[PDB]
Length: 182
Ligand SMILES: [Zn+2]
Image (cartoon, protein in one colour):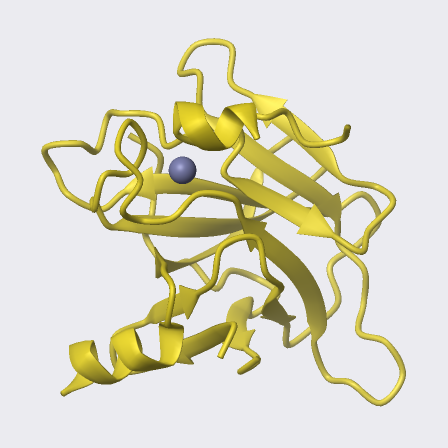
């Protein structure tokens, strides 16, 4: 099982979220609610700047202990529907340097981009993720809750920082957020 323990590390790495309803985040639940294939802005916040060659990895895992060892991937239907391999749940949009990776021993998927510092006028770096299957899809997540783990890594894959958030991919994110909060 991939690690999910929060580790702010030497650079004081944490996550922030931009309300878009296509994407909305509940701090109380540490849970993002989003629509299929739509923009999910995830912000990287650091106290100090990580150095040359730093990478940002995203990986989905099942939250439930009974499915923890199972690989999260798209359902056959959504796989069937030229950068992201069709099996990958998580894509990155708006970035020319996206790497799609598959672990040789675990078969787990991840998507990696280089760390870039914040743009002018911003105090954070925003990455636009897309989730390519609904939480409810049979033969995929099948209503099993997932966690996205965001890892800051050096060029050799060593850990610099780790954060995570739950995700629900659904038709009406604002409504589902309200229900789970209340
Ligand atoms: Zn699906």
